[PDB]
Image (spheres, coloured by chain):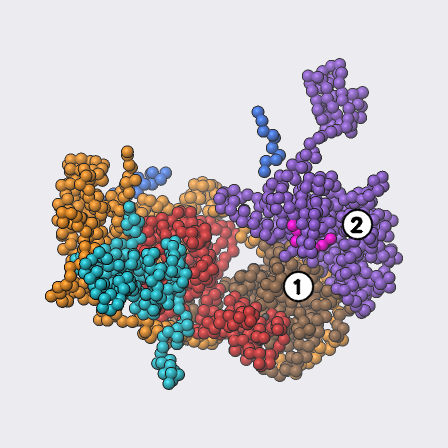
């Protein structure tokens, strides 16, 4: 009914995609998702003539805005493509080429953490700027992540993703997630989709991605209330402990810092805020249930 | 007329009496009512026992209504003789001395409102004859008396009082008084160095 | 004092007061206390706050104020009075109460008493108005005028006390006891008449002063300093906040229930670069028609479940009859109340409540039996048509009750034997 | 109304012509955008899969709340024959048109397009200086000739003929002059997008034997093109069609290469104010507008007295109002123009008036009247004055032998809705000239 | 010089924002909102009237407070006819309080206010609260006089003994007893007694009251609270809820007694266990790890990029550099972003993107 | 604006009862 902005955040990392190719029998599967995303963006632009497109790539050493251009060309797609569609696709491919060159130069750099949270925050900031500038535009976030590569530690991603969830809920900006890899579910991203009215999808095979993109992640903000989401997974809205690394259904959270704990911390002292708990108070919770003698 | 009935709804009424003990108890009651937030109004004589030492600061004194110039009784033989003696000896005019005597008590009552620089109050002189006595008020009161307030109306004075109280109810900026009205040891040393 | 857990639980009058007014609380109470047999103290233990709120509603009174001044008579004149104002008048003027109690049942009724009081000079004197000799007043009320004088003397003695030297005006006049000067002019002395006696205007001033003093003193009922007052606060050191700072360290272990090298990574990167520069076919995105059907089947498989949940995501309309539904709700409510009490006593942590825990466990077992009996009754009456629906309606509470009993049994097995 | 009008015209076209119309991806890209959002979603779902999906599966996607929207979407999609319903094996399978599917696939995936969108000469021109000025001037000339204000360069015989043959701009040779009508005023009240679409639709209906599919190919491709760039020259009919379109100020020719203009992009989708005016209780109008088009259209129902650079001042008079009404303009349309061109001062004062009304009586939500009710009352009263005298053409029936026959004839006339007046006491009645023949035939029978 | 005046005013505004420290704040709050409904509230200084504007802003405050403090609780008291009337019991349901305010807005205010009565009622309402929660009372006072039956100083002493904290928002002028209350009840701090100057400043004060108050160093109540995270259930048939005894399509299952609850966060009606979701706790992490302020870069030095890092927007070119940087990551940000990252978001995109 | 108009011219009671009876029984039991 009204124009909507689509901000696609793609987590393209050589380490992430090499593991996918090695575990599978598909070589260069990254290209497949590139052209699948290109056709998806063309379809989004064909939905209406007043809708914009933004692409943010999260590479090893940071983030980059593939579209629109920064601070103001090779032929990779036929020039017969629609002028508006090509104006975005050619720039996207050129920035992909430049990004690959830049990251190839620093391939030896030891990056121990991903940048998906920063990419999501940048996308939200871009949505805010465009909405404030133009006046009466809807917005939508898409996150294409490669989960095949084993992650080092996802704990540090918890807080920023939750803040992004809150901001998206304030701006009524659904965020959808598409995961390509081995793990069937990503707890944090699935929580993001469920709490922001998004769509969480996990696909094992890179081929035929356009079907999923067109049938599942094509719900524009105008008809979200009238379209039922295809998500199948169910979340628990739980969090892992702080010193045992297990999901806790019932536990103790420190009042001062609201840090979760499955069991009483050793030494009767919080391991995060260095706060000493009262012995008399802590004994009460340690007391066992009452049963007749 | 029933005006005291209207006053009673908003504040308690305490009245100065000839009995010194009763007046002291009235002062204590007025202070208690001002402290507990009930709100109180104290009626006294400008040349009475309260104005000769009792001080109203902070919560105790907020508004001072000087109802008329506290002129002495002109038709008094003692005062007339004193005026004649002063005119003959010190060459002081009778009107000048009478105005001085009244303005002195008016200022005496006015000055019992402020203890420090964080205290505030509204001082209304209700008489047509104060309009020409600005030059006779103390210097620190004359400087604060603006030219637009020389002759006001009751409603306009009420509006000004409301605005002034609302303005004075805000937190003061520390920088606005850091070294211009309140001096620390370093500021005092700087003043001494600049002066020397 | 009185507003405490023990007294609120023991004040049966308050319990009978709020429950008579509140119907829903009575709805639960009738089932859980009359037929079920739950102790009233146990019932109110979890509703302490309701009792305190209902008590505070009626346990508060307005502050003292000048009522006779608010009384405006406004030829006939109509003056309106209310019970609250009558009580305020009695509280503020004990003489009126004295003349009321001894005369209302004896000589004349309350309306006549109030009319005579309003017409009398006593009301004028208590209003702080100058009494006029021309006014006739009332003969009956005037008998108390001298008693009012005596009461005023007694109240003056009640209020008199030593005053601090800071605001001691008596010391100001007694500082020099041998002062002899010129007597003040008549403008500086109380007004007097031709005959030389007082005009009476000072009396009303003293009356209003005494009224204010009495109100302030009544505030202070049964229910060093000079240095602090005289010190200049503005010149003191500015107040400094004493808030505590916190530094939150972040170090948490990962959740608990092939490696690729730089050469392979660079080789794949070179491959993708070469492919992109050489050629790119967007038409290859279209599937082969052998995987499109599978993808569509998977997506529609998810869609069916999502729609089934979404079509049914004021109480919702129900198929059961009103009587049976109400009975089911009653059973659920009583069972839930028993469960709440059982869990409270079980997790109290003190063994002194073992008898209460046992009684609540027996009550829960009886609740299970009652649920089974209701299921059987509905099964036979409705021929299984509504039995399944009722069981679905009451399924979670049955599971909770049986879980509580199972946990109690397991812990008893471990503890006792 | 934009999408509704275009969709209605496209629906009236035969299916045989639609199938050939969907050959070029350029036309498909334009037609796709006009459908409702739900229809667009379904079309995008169906385009990328080469299979048949049952209608029930599509129904599952829509929530209970949007069930109504599902009906409109499916009805609109089926009206254009875009979705071909095939029933077999007891299931009402739904499939997409193969030509439409292939066209969308080519457009989206950059497949073979046969240069439907055209080529680029890489010889750009100054759009602001030349394209904007040319199109603005030409559109202004046509609109000026429509509003009737004198203008030197009269429009070409092509557009003049289209105007006359259309309901717009009624003309009579006996009178020897051209005047605006009710539809003309509505056209002038419509926005630029709808103003262009109306003329283009009239041209589409006017053209006879130049293919209907070719005309839509050219129009939709023109909408596809972007302003400020060159495009080398196409169909044989499209050559003369391009020359004709140059007469509407859409495409600019040097005198080999044609350039689209701002209106070309305006065709595809949409995109103090000029035109806002103040109306006083003294029947005075002060319009803060500087444009001959606005001045001329205001002159229709305003007795202009003077003008300034920044604004135009006039007075409402019975003569001007009667002129506008005689031209067929409705008071509703006049008040619509005034309301949609109300000044911010008038809007703020009317908002304060509504706020005061609701504050005084918030129980009733009174309507928001931007301009004083007296002007509305006066205009409607003048319309009533014009409508005071009512006359009909027909014949009077009397001298009936039998009351039964009189009642029979009068009742038949009432049943066929051609009875205007009757009197039983006089046994007389009057019927319309249209129904005179039917009444006479019934009387004979 | 007007543009430079605007720039210097912006710098002065940022001066206060410069000083930010990770103060310890009590996320778990128990607030008692006391409203004044007396004859003094019939004045027209606030349009249409004080009662109407105050009630509207109270509704908005309730919405914001329960949006940003999911695990807190609120209660509503009013002052009418010199008596304190309770209109909302302490609970975690925002809808009940909103409906209570919608009911309150109708009745005309009359009578005198009673601060002592209101404070006693608030103390009684806050008596049954855990020691780990912060007991707060927000009063909207409009009158210049107080009529009380007892000694207000004794009530103030009792409040100090009970460790309750009182914030007072005045309308016209400072009241001595209000100042003494707000000072003695906040360890001598005198910044908790605010008098508004206009409608916009009243809105700003109401919004400021939302954020949790920092705790005192000497007031230690550190402890561990037993809470559980339930799992949402999707059922085919309606079932009776253990909290309201009403049929609902689905509800969260407690992990300690398996009873179902309609909405979160609420104390379980059976095991008296607090049920919350991870997002409810996540909403308060920014109060424990506030983002450090951003300082503008002087024009003397050389800038990094011509476009904003977070939004990719051209930096306006003209005297004063329109750039803001994050010291942690040293990434230039535009003025439009800075406010968004410091008001809506709570993470720096540059810091998140920088690997370690 | 009246232009189009034609021109002017010529039960809880039992619940309370059982409540009272039960409380009377309670009081008698305590006494
Ligand atoms: Zn901690
Ligand atoms: Zn419920
Ligand atoms: Zn539970
Ligand atoms: Zn940073
Ligand atoms: Zn920016």
Work out whether residue D255 can be spotted: yes
User: Which sits in the foreground, E174 or A50?
Assistant: E174
Disc 1 crowd, CA 10 A, few/some/many (<14, 14-19, 20+): some
Q: Which chain is orange?
A: C
Q: Which chain is cyan?
A: B
Residue shown at 54% from the left, 80% from the top: E356
Q: Is residue D21 magenta?
A: no
The alpha-carbon separation of the residues under discs 1 and 2 comes to 44 Å
* Residue A68 as seen in the image, left or right of residue C377: right
Classify C373 as above or below E140. above
Q: Regarding mark 2 in the picture, which secondary structure is present there? A: loop
* Residue C385 as seen in the image, left or right of residue A183: left
Q: Which chain is blue?
A: F
Classify E21 as above or below E248. below
Q: Which chain is purple?
A: D
Q: Chain of mark 2?
A: D
Indicate the colour of chain E: red
User: Could you say where residue B66 lies in the image, as x and y percent from the top left?
Assistant: 30, 58
* Residue denoted by label 2: D150
Disc 2 crowd, CA 10 A, few/some/many (<14, 14-19, 20+): few
Instruction: Name which quarter of the figure residue A214 lies in.
Output: bottom right
Residue shown at 69% from the left, 62% from the top: A45
Residue shown at 61% from the left, 30% from the top: F6
Which numbered disc covers residue A52? Answer: 1
In front: label 1 or label 2: 2
């Amino acid at each position: 009914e009204s124009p909507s902005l689509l901000t696609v955040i793609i987590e393209i990392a050589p380490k992430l995609w090499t593991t996918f190719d090695e575990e599978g029998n598909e070589k260069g599967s990254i290209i497949k998702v590139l052209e699948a995303l290109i056709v998806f963006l063309n379809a989004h632009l064909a939905f209406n003539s007043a809708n914009k497109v933004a692409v943010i790539a999260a590479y090893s050493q940071g983030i980059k805005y593939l579209y629109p251009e920064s601070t103001s060309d090779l032929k990779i797609i036929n020039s017969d493509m629609y002028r508006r569609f090509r104006n975005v696709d050619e720039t996207l491919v050129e920035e992909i080429y430049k990004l690959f060159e830049l990251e190839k130069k620093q391939i030896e750099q030891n990056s121990q953490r991903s940048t998906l949270a920063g990419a999501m925050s940048a996308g939200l900031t871009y949505v805010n700027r465009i909405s404030k500038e133009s006046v009466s535009l809807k917005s939508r976030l898409l996150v294409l992540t490669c989960g095949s590569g084993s992650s080092k530690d996802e704990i540090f991603q918890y807080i920023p993703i939750m803040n992004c969830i809150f901001s998206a809920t304030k701006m009524k900006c659904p965020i959808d997630v598409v995961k390509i890899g081995g793990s069937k579910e990503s707890t944090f991203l699935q929580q993001t989709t469920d709490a922001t009215n998004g769509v969480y999808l996990h696909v094992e095979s890179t081929e035929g991605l356009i079907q999923y993109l067109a049938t599942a992640m094509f719900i524009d903000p105008s008809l979200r209330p009238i379209i039922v989401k295809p998500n199948h997974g169910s979340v628990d809205f739980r969090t892992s402990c702080y010193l045992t690394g297990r999901v806790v259904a019932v536990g103790f959270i420190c009042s001062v810092c609201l840090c979760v704990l499955s069991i009483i911390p050793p030494g009767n002292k919080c391991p995060a805020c260095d706060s000493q708990f009262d012995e008399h108070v802590i004994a009460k919770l340690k007391r066992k249930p009452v049963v007749p003698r | 007329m029933g005006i005291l009935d209207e006053v009673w709804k908003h504040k308690l009424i305490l009245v100065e009496t000839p009995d010194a003990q009763e007046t002291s108890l009235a002062l204590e009651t007025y202070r208690k009512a001002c402290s507990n937030g009930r709100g109180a109004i104290l009626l006294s004589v400008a040349r009475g026992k309260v104005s000769e030492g009792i001080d109203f600061d902070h919560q105790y004194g907020r508004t001072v209504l000087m109802i008329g110039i506290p002129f002495q009784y002109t038709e008094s033989r003692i005062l007339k003789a004193r005026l004649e003696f002063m005119r003959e000896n010190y060459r002081i005019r009778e009107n000048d001395f009478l105005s001085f005597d009244a303005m002195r008590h008016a200022a005496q009552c006015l000055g019992r409102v402020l203890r420090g620089k964080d205290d505030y109050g509204v001082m209304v002189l209700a008489d047509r004859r104060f309009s020409r006595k600005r030059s006779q008020l103390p210097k620190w009161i004359a400087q604060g008396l603006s030219d637009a307030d020389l002759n006001l109306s009751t409603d306009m004075a009420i509006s000004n009082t409301k605005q002034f109280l609302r303005t004075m109810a805000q937190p003061t900026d520390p920088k606005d008084q850091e070294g211009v009205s309140v001096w620390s040891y370093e500021d005092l040393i700087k003043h001494q160095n600049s002066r020397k | 004092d009185s507003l405490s857990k023990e007294k609120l639980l023991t004040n049966l009058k308050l319990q009978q007061s709020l429950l008579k007014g509140n119907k829903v609380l009575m709805k639960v109470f009738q089932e859980t206390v009359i037929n079920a047999g739950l102790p009233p103290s146990e019932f109110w233990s979890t509703r302490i706050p309701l009792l305190r709120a209902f008590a505070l509603s009626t346990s508060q009174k307005v502050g003292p104020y000048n009522v006779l001044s608010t009384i405006k008579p406004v030829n006939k004149v109509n003056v309106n009075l209310s019970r609250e104002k009558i009580l305020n008048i009695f509280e503020n003027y004990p003489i009126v109460k004295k003349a009321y109690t001894d005369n209302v049942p004896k000589n004349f009724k309350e309306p006549e008493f109030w009319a005579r009081f309003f017409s009398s000079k006593l009301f004028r004197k208590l209003r702080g108005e100058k009494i006029m000799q021309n006014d006739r007043g009332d003969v009956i009320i005037d008998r108390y005028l001298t008693l009012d004088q005596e009461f005023d003397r007694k109240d003056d003695d009640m209020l008199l006390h030593p005053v601090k030297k800071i605001i001691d005006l008596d010391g100001n006049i007694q500082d020099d006891p041998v002062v002899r000067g010129n007597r003040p002019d008549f403008t500086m002395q109380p007004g007097v008449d031709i005959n030389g006696n007082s005009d009476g205007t000072v009396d009303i001033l003293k009356g209003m002063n005494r009224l204010s003093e009495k109100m302030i003193m009544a505030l202070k009922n049964e229910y060093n300093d000079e240095r602090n007052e005289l010190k200049i606060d503005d010149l003191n050191e500015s107040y400094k906040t004493n808030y505590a700072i916190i530094h939150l360290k972040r170090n948490a272990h990962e959740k608990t229930t092939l490696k690729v090298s730089n050469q392979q990574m660079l080789q794949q990167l070179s491959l993708v670069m070469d492919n992109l520069i050489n050629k790119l076919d967007l038409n290859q995105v279209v599937p082969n028609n052998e995987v499109s059907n599978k993808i569509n089947k998977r997506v529609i498989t998810a869609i069916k479940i999502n729609a089934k949940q979404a079509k049914h995501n004021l109480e919702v309309k129900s198929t059961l009859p009103i009587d049976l539904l109400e009975s089911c709700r009653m059973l659920h409510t009583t069972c839930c109340e028993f469960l709440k009490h059982f869990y409270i006593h079980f997790q109290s942590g003190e063994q002194k409540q073992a008898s209460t825990v046992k009684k609540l466990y027996n009550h829960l077992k009886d609740c299970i039996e009652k649920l089974n009996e209701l299921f059987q009754d509905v099964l036979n009456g409705d021929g299984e048509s509504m039995s399944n629906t009722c069981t679905a309606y009451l399924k979670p509470v049955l599971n909770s009750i049986t879980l509580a009993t199972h946990k109690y049994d397991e812990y008893f097995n471990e503890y006792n034997n | 109304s934009l999408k509704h009008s275009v969709t209605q015209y496209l629906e009236e076209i035969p299916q045989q012509v639609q199938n050939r119309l969907y050959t070029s991806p350029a036309t498909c890209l334009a037609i796709y955008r006009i459908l409702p959002p739900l229809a667009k979603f379904f079309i995008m779902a169906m385009v990328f899969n080469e299979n048949e999906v049952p209608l029930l599966d599509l129904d599952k996607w829509v929530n209970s709340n949007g069930k109504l929207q599902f009906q409109n979407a499916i009805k609109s999609m089926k009206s254009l024959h875009l979705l071909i319903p095939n029933k077999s094996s007891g299931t009402l399978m739904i499939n997409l048109n193969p030509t439409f599917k292939i066209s969308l696939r080519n457009a989206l995936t950059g497949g073979e397009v046969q240069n439907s969108f055209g080529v680029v000469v890489e010889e750009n021109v100054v759009s602001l200086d030349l394209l904007d000025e040319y199109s603005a001037n030409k559109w202004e000339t046509i609109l000026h000739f429509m509003v009737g204000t004198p203008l030197a360069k009269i429009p070409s015989e092509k557009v003049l003929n289209l105007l006359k043959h259309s309901k717009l701009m009624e003309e009579v040779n006996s009178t020897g002059e051209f005047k605006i009508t009710n539809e003309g005023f509505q056209f002038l009240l419509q926005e630029i997008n709808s103003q262009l679409w109306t003329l283009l639709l009239q041209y589409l209906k006017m053209i006879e034997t130049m293919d209907l599919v070719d005309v839509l190919h050219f129009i939709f491709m023109l909408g596809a093109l972007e302003v400020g760039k060159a495009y080398k020259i196409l169909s044989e009919t499209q050559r003369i069609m391009l020359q004709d379109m140059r007469d509407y100020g859409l495409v600019f020719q040097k005198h080999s290469i044609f350039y689209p203009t701002k209106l070309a992009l305006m065709l595809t989708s949409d995109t103090i104010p000029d035109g806002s005016l103040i109306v006083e209780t003294n029947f005075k109008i002060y319009s803060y507008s500087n444009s001959p088009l606005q001045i001329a259209v205001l002159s229709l129902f305003v007795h202009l007295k003077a003008r300034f650079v920044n604004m135009v001042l006039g007075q409402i008079t019975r003569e001007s109002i009667r002129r506008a009404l005689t031209n067929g303009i409705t008071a509703d349309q006049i008040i619509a123009y005034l309301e949609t061109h109300a000044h911010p001062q008038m809007r703020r004062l009317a908002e304060e008036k509504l706020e005061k009304k609701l504050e005084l009586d918030p129980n009733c939500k009174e309507p928001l009247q931007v301009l004083p009710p007296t002007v509305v009352d006066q205009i409607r009263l003048w319309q009533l004055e014009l409508d005071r005298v009512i006359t009909y053409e027909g014949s009077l029936y009397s001298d009936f032998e039998t009351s039964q026959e009189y009642n029979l004839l009068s009742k038949y006339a009432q049943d066929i809705g051609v009875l205007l007046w009757k009197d039983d006491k006089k046994k007389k009645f009057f019927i319309s000239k249209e129904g005179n023949s039917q009444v006479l035939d019934f009387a004979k029978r | 010089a007007s543009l430079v005046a605007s720039i210097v005013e912006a710098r002065k505004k940022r001066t206060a924002k410069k000083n930010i420290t990770p103060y310890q704040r009590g996320i778990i709050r128990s607030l008692i909102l006391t409203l004044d409904c007396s004859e003094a509230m019939l004045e027209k200084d606030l349009r249409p009237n004080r009662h109407a504007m105050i009630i509207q802003y109270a509704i908005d405050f309730v919405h914001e407070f329960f949006d940003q403090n999911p695990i807190s609780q609120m209660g509503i008291i009013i002052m009418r006819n010199g008596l304190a009337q309770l209109v909302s019991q302490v609970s975690g349901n925002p809808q009940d309080h909103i409906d209570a305010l919608k009911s309150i807005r109708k009745q005309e205010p009359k009578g005198n206010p009673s601060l002592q009565n209101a404070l006693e009622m608030a103390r009684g309402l806050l008596l049954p609260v855990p020691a780990h929660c912060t007991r707060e009372v927000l009063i909207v006072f409009g009158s210049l006089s107080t009529t009380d039956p007892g000694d207000i100083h004794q009530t103030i002493d009792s409040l100090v003994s009970e460790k309750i904290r009182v914030k007072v928002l005045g309308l016209s002028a400072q009241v001595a007893i209000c100042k003494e209350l707000c000072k003695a009840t906040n360890y001598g701090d005198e910044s908790f007694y605010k008098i508004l100057l206009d409608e916009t400043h009243l809105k700003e004060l109401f919004n400021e009251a939302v954020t949790p108050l920092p705790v005192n160093k000497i007031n230690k109540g550190f402890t561990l609270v037993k809470m559980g995270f339930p799992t949402r259930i999707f059922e085919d048939t309606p079932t009776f809820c253990s909290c309201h005894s009403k049929l609902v399509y689905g509800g969260y299952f407690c992990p300690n007694c398996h009873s179902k609850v309609c909405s979160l966060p609420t104390v379980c009606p059976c095991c008296d266990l607090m049920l919350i979701l991870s997002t409810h706790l996540a909403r308060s992490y920014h109060h424990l790890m506030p983002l450090k302020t951003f300082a503008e870069v002087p024009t003397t030095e050389k800038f990094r990029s011509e476009d904003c890092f977070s939004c990719q927007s051209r930096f306006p070119i003209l005297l004063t550099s329109s750039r803001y940087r994050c010291e942690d990551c040293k990434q230039e940000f535009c003025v439009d972003c800075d406010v968004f990252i410091h008001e809506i978001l709570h993470n720096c995109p540059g810091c998140e993107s920088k690997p370690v | 604006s009246t232009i189009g108009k034609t021109a002017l011219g010529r039960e809880e009671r039992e619940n309370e009862k059982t409540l009272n009876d039960y409380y009377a029984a309670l009081a008698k039991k305590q006494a």
